[PDB]
Length: 11
Image (cartoon, rainbow, N blue to C red):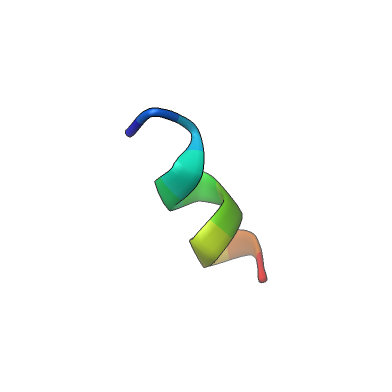
């Protein structure tokens, strides 16, 4: 979602 979720998951 909005690329923000992916960032959170990756970290």
